[PDB]
Image 1: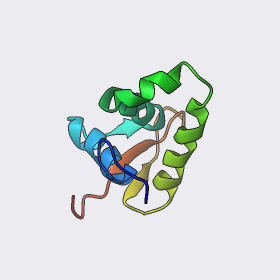
Image 2 (image 1 turned 90 degrees about the vertical axis):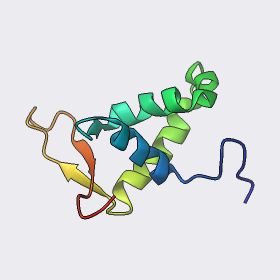
Image 3 (image 1 turned 30 degrees about the vertical axis):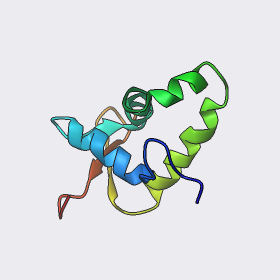
Length: 90
């Protein structure tokens, strides 16, 4: 309701852009976080503060909710599961 500024875009859309931006089309959980700061500098100010741990959890709900994302079995012995968009469309 009070969304504005860069755009009332949903986080699912911003996460899709990051994966779509990558060539292999694959990113780990930590990469989404770093990419958001890169694709959304407005978060650089919070990086110097603990408040960073807040918005990061919100993203975690999107990864679990909306099967839009598929889980990948990391060969690194499940060190960091890779997130990918479903190939049925996108």
